[PDB]
Each structure stands twice: as C-alpha cells, then as structure tokens.
Amino acid sequence: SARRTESDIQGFHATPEFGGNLQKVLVDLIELSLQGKQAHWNVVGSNFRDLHLQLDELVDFAREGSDTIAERMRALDAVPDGRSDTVAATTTLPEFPAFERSTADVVDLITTRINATVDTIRRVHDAVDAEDPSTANLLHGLIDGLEKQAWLIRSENRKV
Amino acid sequence: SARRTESDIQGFHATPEFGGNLQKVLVDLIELSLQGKQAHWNVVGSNFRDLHLQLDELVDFAREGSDTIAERMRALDAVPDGRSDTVAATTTLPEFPAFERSTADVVDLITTRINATVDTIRRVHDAVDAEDPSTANLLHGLIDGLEKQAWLIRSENRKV
Amino acid sequence: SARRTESDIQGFHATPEFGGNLQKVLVDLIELSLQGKQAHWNVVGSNFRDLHLQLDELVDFAREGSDTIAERMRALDAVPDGRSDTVAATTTLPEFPAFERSTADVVDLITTRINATVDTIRRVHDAVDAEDPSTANLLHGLIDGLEKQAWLIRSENRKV
Amino acid sequence: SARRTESDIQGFHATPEFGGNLQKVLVDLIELSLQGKQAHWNVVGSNFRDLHLQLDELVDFAREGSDTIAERMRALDAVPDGRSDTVAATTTLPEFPAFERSTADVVDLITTRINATVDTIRRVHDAVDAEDPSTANLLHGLIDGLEKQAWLIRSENRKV
Amino acid sequence: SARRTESDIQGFHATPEFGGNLQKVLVDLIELSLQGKQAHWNVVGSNFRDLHLQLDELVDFAREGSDTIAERMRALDAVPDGRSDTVAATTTLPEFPAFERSTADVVDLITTRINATVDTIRRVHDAVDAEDPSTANLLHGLIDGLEKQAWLIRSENRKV
Amino acid sequence: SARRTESDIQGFHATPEFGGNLQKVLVDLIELSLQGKQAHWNVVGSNFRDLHLQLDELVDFAREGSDTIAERMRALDAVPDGRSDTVAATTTLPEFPAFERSTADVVDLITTRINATVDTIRRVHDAVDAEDPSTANLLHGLIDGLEKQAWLIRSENRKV
Amino acid sequence: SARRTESDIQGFHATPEFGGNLQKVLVDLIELSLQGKQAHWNVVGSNFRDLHLQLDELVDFAREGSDTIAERMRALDAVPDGRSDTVAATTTLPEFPAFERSTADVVDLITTRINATVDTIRRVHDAVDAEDPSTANLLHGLIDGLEKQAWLIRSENRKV
Amino acid sequence: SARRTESDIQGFHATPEFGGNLQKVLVDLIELSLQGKQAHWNVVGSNFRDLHLQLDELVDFAREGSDTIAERMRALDAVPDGRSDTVAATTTLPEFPAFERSTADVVDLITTRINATVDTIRRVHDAVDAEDPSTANLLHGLIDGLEKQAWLIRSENRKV
Amino acid sequence: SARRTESDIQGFHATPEFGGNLQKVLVDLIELSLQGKQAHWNVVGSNFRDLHLQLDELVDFAREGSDTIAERMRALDAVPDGRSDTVAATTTLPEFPAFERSTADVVDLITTRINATVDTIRRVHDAVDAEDPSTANLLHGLIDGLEKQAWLIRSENRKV
Amino acid sequence: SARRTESDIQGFHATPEFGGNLQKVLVDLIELSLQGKQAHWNVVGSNFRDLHLQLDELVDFAREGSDTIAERMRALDAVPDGRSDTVAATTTLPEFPAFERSTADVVDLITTRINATVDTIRRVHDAVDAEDPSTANLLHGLIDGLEKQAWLIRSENRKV
Amino acid sequence: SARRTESDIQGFHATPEFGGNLQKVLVDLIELSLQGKQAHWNVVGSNFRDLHLQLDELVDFAREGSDTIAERMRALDAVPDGRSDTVAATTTLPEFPAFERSTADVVDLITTRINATVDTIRRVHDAVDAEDPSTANLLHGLIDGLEKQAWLIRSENRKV
Amino acid sequence: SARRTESDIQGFHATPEFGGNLQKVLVDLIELSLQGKQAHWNVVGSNFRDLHLQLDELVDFAREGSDTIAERMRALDAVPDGRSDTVAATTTLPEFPAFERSTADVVDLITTRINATVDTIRRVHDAVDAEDPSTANLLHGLIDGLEKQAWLIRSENRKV
Ligand SMILES: [Cl-]
Ligand SMILES: [Cl-]
Ligand SMILES: [Cl-]
Ligand SMILES: [Cl-]
Ligand SMILES: [Fe+2]
Ligand SMILES: [Fe+2]
Ligand SMILES: [Fe+2]
Ligand SMILES: [Fe+2]
Ligand SMILES: [Fe+2]
Ligand SMILES: [Fe+2]
Ligand SMILES: [Fe+2]
Ligand SMILES: [Fe+2]
Ligand SMILES: [Fe+2]
Ligand SMILES: [Fe+2]
Ligand SMILES: [Fe+2]
Ligand SMILES: [Fe+2]
Ligand SMILES: [Mg+2]
Ligand SMILES: [Mg+2]
Ligand SMILES: [Mg+2]
Ligand SMILES: [Mg+2]
Ligand SMILES: [Mg+2]
C-alpha cells in the first residue's frame, strides 16, 4: 500500500570530492598512528611510563578512527588509499624525528601532530557536513577524541 | 543564588509532524528487522554462512534502532505504533519475496531494502533536525550503521 | 565393517503439515514480540519501570523462541514465513490496542496474549510430538518459558 | 610531500562565552547528580525499589555527563569549576527538599529538576553549535540521555 | 485475520494431584540441599577437599532445581510450601546425621539421599507427564543432573 | 634465629559458649533463607516484581551468611547443624504463613523476620567479640547487610 | 514424619540393551568428531573459511555430545567404550576420504555423516525412551543440535 | 519451639548523636569527591597523567564511601543530607582553589583534604563504635581506604 | 625501491618427510585424547574426582595440541590424517584397557601413555628442528605441557 | 562556615611499637607464602592434586595479606622489610623441610605453619587494636582467612 | 653468601647488524599491516565477508608482531624506525595495487605479501639466533602465526 | 598396529647439573620478586605511581617465572628449593637496601637486579639447551620478559 514498487532502489552515493575529503582525513589518521607508535617505542626520560601508555591509547584511537573513516568511504562507495607510499606522499603532518627522544620533546612533538590531524578534520568539516551530516557526526567524534588526547598529553609540559 | 523557583518545569514536546516523521522511521526499521530475519532463515547457496550471519547483525542493529526511535518518541511525548498491522500497512519497503532465495538474490533484495530504510531517514532528516538537533544525531547513527550494513552485504555481488 | 556403504544418506524430512504446525507457532511468537515491544514503549502509570523491564524480558524470550522455531523448520527443510503481512494476516493473538495504556491494563492485555501464544503451542503439540519428539522438546521449553512470563506479569494484578 | 612545516601548531581554543556556556551546563549536571543521590537515599513508599534503582542510573548518567563537559572544557583551554560553593551559588535547578519524600513526590521533584538541566543545555545549544559543532554533538547525547531519564521516571505518575 | 476475540484467556491450571506431586519433589530437593550443605561443612578425612567441593555443586544444582519446581507450580496456579517445618515433616529422605562424618561415610550417606530424591521424581514422573509433558521435561533435567551427581560422588567409594 | 622449634602448633578453638552462639546465628540465617524463598515464590499484588527480585537478593545474602558462619565454626573446631529438623525446632523467627500473600503483607512479614535474625546476631555479639574479635567482624558484615535488606524491603510500605 | 529408613537406596540401573544403544550413539558421535576435524583441516576452495569455522562448531557440539552420552552411561552404571579401535570397528558412518577435498565435496560428505549420526540416535530413540525418558531428552538435544549443524553446512550446496 | 510470637519486631535505630556523627562523615566524603574531581580536571604539569588517574580512583572510593554512609543512615532510620548547599555550609575541608594548579600543588592540597576527611572519621569513631560496632566496621574500611589514597598521592612530593 | 618486483612469491614448503614426522605426532596426540576421555569416564575409586578433572585438562591440552600440529602441517602444505582407522592403525601408544579402572591403575596407565606421546615428539624433534626451527618451537610447547601433565598425574602414586 | 583554614593537615602515623608489630605479621606472611610454594611444588602421594591446588590458594591469600600489611605500614608512615635475609632471620615459623614430602606430612607441616602465622597476628592483635582499630580490622580478615585455610588443609588428615 | 657486589650491572646489547636485522623485520610487518587494511577495505566479490574478516585478523597479528619486534629492539638498546617514509623506502614487499580488487585477486596478492614478510624473517633468522636465541623464539612465533594466516587466506583460491 | 608394548614407559629425567642450573635460575627469580615488592612498597618521590605500578608487573612476571621453572624441575624429576634461607644464602642478586628509596634510586637498583637475574639465565642457557631444548624455550620467555621490564623501568632515568 505505502510500499514502494521499485525492484532496485539506489543508496546514497558520495561525490568524488566528498571521497577526496575523507581521504585527506584518512592519511593524517594513519600517519598519526604510525608517528604515535614511533613515539611510544622511542620515548625516554622523566615520566617515561605515563607517556608510553598514553601514546598507545592515542594510537588505539587513531587506528579506530582510520577504520571509521575508511569504512564510511566504502559505505558511500568511495575507495580509500591507506598504503604507505600514499600516506607518506600526501600527509600534512610534520615528519616525526628519528632516534630516542625525551619525554618533554615527545609531548610537544605529538601535541603538534594531533593538532595537525584535527586541523585537517576541521578544514574539511563544512564541505562534508553540507553533503552528508551523518559523516560530519563521525568527524565530531574524531575531533572530540583527538582534542582530548592533545589535552591529556600536552598537560605534562604545562607550567602554572 | 541562581536557582529557579518553579515547582513545575515541563519538558520538550514534539509537534505532531515530528512525531509522524519518527513514526515513518520506526515502521521501516521494524519492517527491515522482519525482512532481515526472513532472509537470514531462508537464504541458500554459495556463501550461505556469511550472509546468514551478516543478516543477523543487520537485524540486531535495526532492532536496536527501532528501540532508539520509539523511546525518543516517548521522551518527547509522542506515541509509537509498532504493531504488525500498522507496519504492514505503512512501511515504504518493497515486500520481501516468499520462500527460499539464493545468496545472490538475498544480497540484492536486502541491499535495496536497507537503501529504502535509509532513504526514509534521509527524507525526514532536515525536518527533524530543524525541530530537534539531538534527535537528528540519533538519525545520523542510524544512517551510518545501516549504510555500513549495506556495504558489508552488497559487496558479495560487486564484481571487479 | 559396521560402516554404511551409502555415498548419499538422507536426513529427516518434515511433512508439510508438520512445517505448517511450526509456522502457526512462529507467527504467534513474532506477533507476541511485536505486541510486547508496543506495550514496553507505551505502558504508563503505577509500577511503570517493573513492567517496562519485564516486557523487554518477555520480548527477548519470544524473539529467541521465534529463532528456535524458524531454525528448526529449516533444519527439517520446512520454510518459515515471518514477514509482517503474513504475521498480521495469520496470527491468532488479539490485536494490541493503540496509544498509551495503564500498567494495570497492560498486565491484563499481555497476560492474555502470552496465554494465546501458549495455547497455539499446546494445540499443535501432540501432532508435532507424534512426528518428531525432538521438536516437542523445543515446544516444552517455549511453554515453560512463556508460562513463567505469564505468572511474572499477571502477579502484579493479583489480589489476595 | 604535503607535510606541514610548523613545530608548534596550537589547538582550537574556546571563547570566554563558550567556556561560560559549558560551565553553566556543568554546574547543573553536578547539582542534578547530587540531588539524584539525595532522592535515591531518601525516597520511600509505593514502588520504592524501582525509583531507588532508576535514580542511581540517572546519577550515573549525570556524573558521566559532568566528566564529559569538564574534559571538553579542558580540551578547549577552558577551566571548569565544579566546587560545592560554586555549584550551590550558580545552579539553576530548584532546590531539592531535605528528609524522606514519597515516591510520587520524588517522581515530580526529579522530573522537574531533570527538565531544568535539559533546559540549560537547550538554552546554550545554538551558541555552542555556532562556535564548535563537535561540542554540540556532546550536548545532543546529554539531551537525549536526560530526556530518556525524565520519561522513565515521570511515567510512574502518569494517569491513563 | 485469524485473530482471536477474547480479552481474558486463562492459563493452564494444574490439578490438585499435579500440584501435590510437584510439592513432593520440591520438599525432597530442599531437604537434599540442606543435607548437602550439612555434609559440605562437616565432612572430614581422606579426600576431604574433593567431596567438600562436589557437595557444593550438588547443593547449587538442588537449589536451582527447587526454584525451577516452585516457579513451575506458580506458573500453573499451584502454591509451593518450602518452609522448614513442612520440609522436615514431609521429606522422604533419610535423616542426615549430625556432627563430623568421614569422607567414606559422607559418600555413602549422600549417594543414598540423592537416590531417594531421584526416586521421588521417578515416582511422580508418569502422572506429571500425562497431565503436562512440558513439566516432565523439567523433571528429566532434574533426574539427569542428580543422577550425574550420584555418579560423581559414589565413584569415590568404588572397589575395582 | 626467631624460628619456633615446635613440631605441632595447635589452632585457636572455640569454647562451647562460642560454638553455641554461632549455632544460634546459623539457624536463624537458614530459616530466613527458607522463608525468603517462600515469600519470593508466593508474593502477589502491587509491585510484585520489585519484591520478588529483592527477596532473591535477601536469600542470596542469607545463604552466603550461613556459609560464612558455618565455615567459621569449622575453622574454630565447632560443628554446625543446619538440618531442617534442627532449624525448625530451634529458630527464633516467627513462622511464615502458608499460601499466596500480598506484597504489603510480605513486606511487613519479611521485615519482621529480618529484624528477628539481626536481633539474634546483636544478642550474641558482645560474647562473641569478647572471645574472638575476628568473628565479631563477620557478625558486623551480617548486621550491616541484613539491616540494608530490611530498609530496602520495608520502605515499600512507608507512608509520608 | 515421612522419612524413609533404608540405609542403602540403590540408583536406576540401565539394562544391557540400553547400555548397548547409548554405546552405538557414542561411537558415531566420536567418529563424527574425528571426521569433522579432518574436514576442518583439509577443506580447500570457494568459501573455505566459512566451512572451516562451521566444522569446528560441529566438532565442539559432537564432542560435548559424546561427553553427555558417556557420562549418562556412567550415571546409569553402564560402561562406555570410546577407544579408537572400537570406534573404527563399530561406527556406522561412511569413512571420510583421505587428503584435501573441495568445499562442495566437504559440504556433501559431512552432511551425509551428520545424517548418519542422527539416524543412529533416531533408530535407538524409542527403545531408550521406553526405559528412561530422561535419557531420551538428551537424545532430543543431540538430534536438534546436529540437524541444525546439517542445515548450516548443507545450505552452501543448495541451489535456488 | 523457640519461635518468637511477636507480629511486629522493630529494627535497631540510630540515636540523634549517631545520626549526626554519620552526617559529619557524609558531607566530608561528598566534599572530598567534589574537590577530587576539580583537581582531576584542573591538574597540570610534571607527572600529570599519574595524578589525573589517581585522583579519579580517590573520587571513586569517596563516592562509594558516601553511598555506604548514607545507606547505613537509612538502614538505622536516620536521614542523610548530601545536597550542595549543606555540603558547602557544613564541610570541615579547606576550600579547593580555583583555576589550573600544578601537580606539586595538587599533591599537597589533596593530601591535606584527604587527611581532613579521615580526621572527621577518626574524631567520630569511638562514639559510633560505642553505639554500633557494625558501623565502626564501615568506618574502618573508609579510614584504611582513604589513608591508602593519601599515601599513593603524597609520595609524589617526597624527597629522600 | 627495496620492494621485490615479483608478482608471485612462494612461501615455505615442507618436505614430505617433514609432513610425515608431524603426522606421527598428530596420531599420538589424537590417540592420547581418546584414551584420556576413556580414562576420564571410566576411572573409579579413591580420589576419583581429582583424576576425573585432571584427565579432562590433559584431554584439553592434547586436543589443542592436535589442532596446533595439524594446522602447522596445513600452513606448510602437508596434509594431516586424523581419521579413526589411521589413528588406530598407526599410533605408538599402548592400547588403553576396557571397563572401569581404579584410580591407581589409571594414574600408571595414563602416565605411560603421556610418556609415549612425548617420546614420539622427542624422536622427531631433531629432524623437524633441522628443516624448520619454528615448528620445533611448537614441539617444545607440547613437550613442556605434556610432561607437566605427566607430573601432575603420576604424583598421586608416588610414595616418599 | 565549618571549613578548617589549615594549609597542612597531617595524617595519622604509627608509633614504633605499632610499626614493629606489623613488621612481625609481615615476615610470617611472606615466610608462609614461601613455604606454601615449596610445599605446593614438592608434595607427592595420595590426594596430591587437591593439596597442590589448596596450597596455591593459601599462597594467594598470604601474598595478598603481605601486600595489605606492608601497604598499611606505608599508609601510616612505617617502613616494611620483606627482603629474604630479614624474613629468614626474623620469621617465627618452623623451617620447612627440603625434598619431596608426602601429602600426609605436608598437611601436618603446613597446618602447623599456618597456625604459627595466625598466632603472631593474635599475639599482636590487642596492641594494634588499642592504637588503631582500623588496622585491627585488617588483622581480622587475615585471621579469618588463614584459619579457614588451616581447616581446609588439616581436614585431609582427620580420622573419625 | 653468593651475592654479587657490583652497583652497576649492564644489560645485553645488540650489535648494529642485529639491530638492522630486526629493523628489516619491523618495516615488512608494518607494511603488511598497511596492505592488509587496504585489502580489508577494498576487497569486493564472491566471499567478500570471509576475506574482509580474515584480513582484519591478519592485521591484528602483524600489528602485535611489529610491537613485539620494536619493543625487543628497545630492550636490547636498538632503535626502531617505523615511520611511513622509512617503511615505504625500505620494505621488501611488492606494492599493493590501488582501488577495489576482487576476492580472488586479494587472496593471491595478500598471500604473496605474507610470503614476502615471512621470507624476510626466515632470511634474518640464523643471524638473529646466533646472537640471541631468545629473539629467535619471537621470530618463530611470527613465522608460525603468519604462515597460518597465509593458509587461512590462500585456501579460498586452492582448487581440488 | 604400530602400538608399543611396555606398561611402564619412564619420562625424561634431568641430570644433577641440569637441576642445579634450573635451581640457580629459581632462587634469582624468587629473590627478584621479593626485592620487587620491597621496592614497590618503599619507593617515593617524582613519578612514584608509575614505578609503584611497573614494579608490581615485574613481581607478577617474576612469580609466574619462578612457578614455571620450579614446575619444569618437577616434571623432569628435579627438586626445587625456594625456601627463604636457601634464597638468601644462594641468590646472586646484589642485596636490595632497606627503608624508603627515591624513584631515581629504585630505577637504578632494580634495573641492576633484573640484569643480574637475566645474566643467570643467559649463563645457564647453553647447558640447558644442550640437554633439553624445550626447557631453553622457557628460558627464552624469561629473558624476553625480564629484559622488557628492564627497558620499561630504566627508561625513566635516561638522559636524551
Ligand atoms: Cl528491577
Ligand atoms: Cl564468520
Ligand atoms: Cl598508569
Ligand atoms: Cl578441584
Ligand atoms: Fe575497518
Ligand atoms: Fe526499548
Ligand atoms: Fe535465527
Ligand atoms: Fe573525567
Ligand atoms: Fe526462584
Ligand atoms: Fe560453605
Ligand atoms: Fe566428560
Ligand atoms: Fe546508594
Ligand atoms: Fe584446528
Ligand atoms: Fe602492594
Ligand atoms: Fe608496543
Ligand atoms: Fe606453580
Ligand atoms: Mg564465506
Ligand atoms: Mg516496581
Ligand atoms: Mg571490625
Ligand atoms: Mg607518571
Ligand atoms: Mg582429591
């Protein structure tokens, strides 16, 4: 009665631009995960353990975030690229330095890299929201979670 | 002292239109749940097990979704109708066919029905968001979750 | 030695009548689940919370029951029909009323609907047991569980 | 290489008005949690246990909510004040009465105070959303959750 | 529409003899659980710990069994009596002795008392099954479980 | 250097008075458990479910309590007697009435029986504490736990 | 006082025929377990993973089933023989073929072997039920569980 | 034989002095909880994370403690007052300062406030123990738990 | 750059001799599992329960071991044979005797069968290690676990 | 209004006598833990498994006990010494013998050593209670727990 | 006294070659992780779901493996480099192709890449084992785990 | 039939030197666990909590390690000696100091003592491996785990 008589109903298709916007978020989340693990392993000095542990929590969040974004792309028939070459060639994050780094340095370095990642999400937000508010919801989750990590990490170096 | 002195403070009340819009979402979520179980029981053929299992995950999400929407109606002083006669008389989803269906047919059929359910949510979205953004947030969760199910189901039939 | 030399041994096949008998149970279990959720959402008044919660437990049991019955049908190569139109057209349960209902009314209404569902299982029991005692075992579980729910719900309205 | 150069990328900082708006939400959430426990301990009469238990769920939600808001403030460089004197001096919630209170009275009292808490969040919503949609997402969760609690609690006193 | 009309469909009610038969099972289950704890506390000697632990498992099973039977009585409009005076006055189990008892003695004593409990259930089985096969299903679980306990306990005293 | 050279070091053992006092606690705990289940099964009327559930929680605590006391006796070379005849013959608890009882009646009946049980523990407390403060600690747990149960149950019948 | 005064009460003893009948069930359950693992390890081809996993679930059920039957024999003073030589010499199941087998062949092969195992249980059912209905209940569980496995496995090969 | 024949047996009730003493403990526990969260949110500097985490554990314990004391009051017919105005007006704890505070400062501040809370419990201990040793047991748990928290926190600022 | 330009890279292939060596381990693990269950069911006498339980733990380990070995064979493209006929025809373990066996006898019997199984693993160890050290690692796990079981079981019969 | 204005509020600290008394408990708990493991590893003979398992449970409790006492010392500004040399030099426990020991011997040996440990706690109890009843509470837990362990172990060698 | 008297005892230090060898393993494990996710997101076609899920299990193992290797480097005073640029510049794995790939192609592609990763571990094995057998043990775990993944993935494409 | 004949197949027995080498590892593991707890309780100063927690993880690992070694000795017919006097008299670990120690000092002290424990295992490794590779596998786990702990602890004191 109210039933649609259509045998093939199409779902929501993302524009290629929308897919490209999520791709920008994806590579920065993957890069953040890789840099987070680098910091996690190579951090040394005063309050090593807290930072070591907090960095793993950041990596967990960024990895879950990259899944969320890539899966959202797929749901809307965009196609993600999380390969190493693409991530290195297109990430906006400043390169993480090599070798052992002090806890103080790692705090400042990782805070900057989190903030860079959040900036990318904030930059594409309005364009994403305009096409698909449901995806903007996912972006809000990432912004909230990453900005929480930034606070939890940077607070170590704060002097009051 | 910033304390209010009213003995009676009323809650947010949904308009009849708003109530009607959530009712539209509700009946399609219940119908999708019922069709999902039908497909889950009656699918046979190549890759039976994967689809059988994925369909149960779809049903779980749709059932949780119907609860969310119905409870949201109740919170806003609206009254849901999820009775079988009402669902059958008012759902926009094409009827699920009777008897055993092949994996390939079930994939196509259910994808269309998920697409139809999501279309209803997308159709009422802006009107809901205009009156109550907090409810639109719930709708974003439903859209994201269902379109993910559509991807996980439909990909069986996608060739190269 | 004692091994059967048969390359293709057939399993137990249910008669169509047996399948039809389980189908009667299936539609009443599905209808009970739908009515239970309707009551769960729309119940109001004294002792709201207990009934709200108990009704969800009833729905959980009826949903698990419908899976059990439909899966048993499939195991014996019967084909279930749990679609909304079929449920509405063939259920023996009295229609659940629309709108908010008092806890006292809901208690009486749902007790009657549980008892109707149990009656269907009791009605087909002997015919089912005669063909397949193993399925009668499943029916015993449903009778026991539903009659427990009837007691737990109806006790609210009992005056001694 | 699309890598950014800067070593000190600063995070999103909230305006004083934004921090002030989240502070308003925070004090009302803390007050609600304190009032919720007061009601939880001191409620007596018909259907005591259900209300006793539901009030604990409300408190749990309000406490998680206060953490969410205070932490969001910290993430955005704002400073929460959840101290007893501040909460008492600035909460908009009508004072909860001391001593034992009937279930019927507690239902009415707590519903009013939940509605007051929600009103604060609804009042600041648009200003919060205008500056930071990600924070508005957190507000939506709070509105949804608290309005659910209001329904679950107030339904006890409903007439027909 | 195959919907029934009646608003007050009554449930299956047990005959006085049926309730009496379940009452017989109930008192022997409660007595066994009390005797099981008595043995659990007071057993001493070679292989104490194994018997101590196994007796607790027996008690657990007997207690769950008593709940099952008493609740089944309630479901079928019968009224259990599990009070201490009634249990003592009507149990068919041989009295368990007071004071410390050897493991070997406890094995023999408890095996006899389990067997007595099973005998009661076996004695009422056919009359229960004739009136209500669903209840006989519950009896089968009790027979199976208790006879397993008897084997696990008595095997301690076996010769070759 | 400080090692004792004794081959057999004996444990602290209870005096006959002490053993007798714990036995008094034991029988009232078992009797409360038995009456608790009787009430649990046979309670009917307004707010049935809450009382039904709370009575099971009371029984769980009383059962754990009886184990605690009986095991403490065994630890101190005393012998418990939790057999039905002994419990019925020596309990100080007023007899629980037969048949179905209203929720209001069960509240008053059970509150009285909990209070009787606590009175027994309070009556023996000082004598127990004088001989063995470690056992008095166990009594404090029981008093606290049972008096909480009394509050949670009795509050149903309070009118303010 | 309704207490029995026998110092020795014997348990239910199975006849040799009954013991033999359960032994027939046991050897086919063990053989099915062994063949299930063989198939699980050696299946290759289209939809490998689903079958690999489902076969492990079948093995788990058959192993649990063999335990149930063997323990039931022990409870009734019968003596199981699950040794490899006996299983190989007395199983009624057709031999599982050697080496790697295709998914399609494994589906057909295992379905036949489940069918064979269930046939043994159905063949001995009435004789078992006549002597001991409680054991027949266990058989009903085995029939239901195994025929469910047969459906979940065989449906891979069922076309339209 | 030993059964009391009283229809109404009353529970142990707190004297006004006793109720007053527990109220004193209650407000300091709630105040500690509130200051604990304030410190948790606003702590910054060296070893932020450890302190952030430890303060949450302190708050969890203080919250459980406040429930314990308030529930104990209710059990003994006393009425708690945990409202914000009352806590602020009657707490003995030194006020927690506003704004961000260094880890070193928070360690000293919180240690002092924990000690103040414990002092209150130690001050009321003997009077509580004299009237009701069972409640003194609860006080012992609180003293032990809070003094552990003080050690775990203060140790950060120790120099040896 | 360092990337291999090969479109099809082959994995490690086990020699047929290596596969045959793992096959020897596999049949003895399967035989040990079958004999362990035989002992588990049929053991009687002093300390029945401990042995009954320990034998199940041995069986669990041997079953997990057989999976490990068979899966390792498959990973390296060997093909396991765990069929009943093959196990009986090729196992090196002495046959387990029929009928009920005393705990003392079972201890000695099972210790010998564990030791036989370990001997097979030790016999093939060097040949396995020489081709694939990673598989020798798995053998070390089995040797350690089985030799632990041998100690735990045999200790029952040790006289010092 | 009632707020203390002190900047530094000090915690309760143990006197040298108190610290010394807890140290005495600490070394006997650690020694018991060490002997418990020695017995656990080296026990052989009849009922090996039960004793092996029970000794591990004893060790778990003694280890938790040692943590409790040492942490209590730290909370009260006392310094524990649980080093091997100190434990060996100052423990009151009779030395555990070397080599394999029979189950009968281990039962007697360990019971004696548990009793020695409890004696130490009972000897210091009153002095501890006089200074700090909160710590006496911890001692009550240890006495109760260890005396339970003594009962569970010693009962093996009892003959009645 | 066998105690050493050095105030400083250094740990095992890896040679530069050893560090380099683990670095080779690390970059291929990270690359495999990244390629695994790419395949997981972008696979479409027959048996999509099984591969999608299995690829996630592969990624989990490879991520855990990279952690193990990097942490082992840190333990032995070596410094890992898991940054994207380094992984892309130094991995031996063939590049994963862009865009959607069929199930069959993904099976072949990923199998080759697992084979490549395992080859690196096998290539460095002997050099690692020669310097530090404990690290070789970790390598054995990686080889076993990855070759198992290769089997579970590749078997989809293996025909008869 | 490839079945062996012997009824008494003996297990692998360790040489006196082998048992002696495992005894060396055992005493150093027990000593480390005792020193670890000493440090855990008595550490104070900057980053107390992290070290406090990490030291407990070390103790957990060392205790599991000691069980592993002692049980392996038992499996191979060797007899462990983990008694306090033996540990003190034969441990190679430098004595841990008494009293409170700074975090910086504890980091250096514990790192040295972990390294000493690892050195013992590294010293006996080749002789253990030569006689029994399966035991060397256990040593590898210990080396890996302890060297990880050393890194996690020592990194606190690292400079740049
Ligand atoms: Cl509830
Ligand atoms: Cl799956
Ligand atoms: Cl931490
Ligand atoms: Cl056990
Ligand atoms: Fe994903
Ligand atoms: Fe719901
Ligand atoms: Fe189902
Ligand atoms: Fe928080
Ligand atoms: Fe019950
Ligand atoms: Fe007990
Ligand atoms: Fe079994
Ligand atoms: Fe509470
Ligand atoms: Fe396997
Ligand atoms: Fe500790
Ligand atoms: Fe890691
Ligand atoms: Fe151990
Ligand atoms: Mg599949
Ligand atoms: Mg209620
Ligand atoms: Mg006390
Ligand atoms: Mg720290
Ligand atoms: Mg035993």
Image: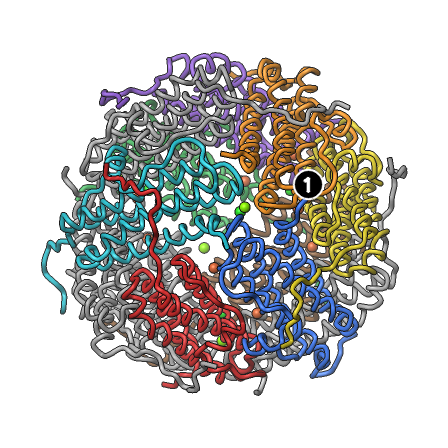
Chain colours: B orange, C yellow, D purple, F brown, G blue, H green, I red, K cyan
Crowding at dot 1, Cα within 10 Å, few <14 / some 14-19 / many 20+, comes out as many
The image quadrant of residue G59 is bottom right
Along the viewing direction, whichever of D125 and I147 lies nearer the viewer: I147
> What amino acid type is highlighted by mark number 1?
Arg
Give the residue at x 64% y 35%. Answer: B63
Q: Is residue H23 above or below residue B131?
A: below
Question: In this view of the protein, can residue H90 be seen by the observer?
Answer: no
Q: Is residue F53 above or below residue B11?
A: below
The image quadrant of residue I78 is bottom left
Q: Residue G94, percent across and down?
A: 62, 68
Q: Is residue G20 above or below residue C56?
A: below
Residue under pointer 1: B101
Along the viewing direction, whichever of K2 and F42 lies nearer the viewer: K2
Question: Quick check: C133 left or right of I81?
Answer: right
The image quadrant of residue B43 is top right
Along the viewing direction, whichever of H103 and I103 lies nearer the viewer: I103
Residue projecting furthest to the left: K6
Along the viewing direction, whichever of I18 and D121 lies nearer the viewer: I18
Give the residue at x 30% y 69%. Answer: I127
Q: Residue I142, percent across and down?
A: 38, 67
Question: In this view of the protein, can residue F48 be seen by the observer?
Answer: yes
Question: Quick check: C89 left or right of I9?
Answer: right
Label 1 element class: strand
Count all numbered tags in the image, as a single digit. Answer: 1
Asked whether mark 1 and ligand 7 are closer than 8 Å, the reply comes as no
**Chain name for mark 1:** B
Q: Residue I112, percent across and down?
A: 42, 81
Q: Residue H3, percent across and down?
A: 71, 62
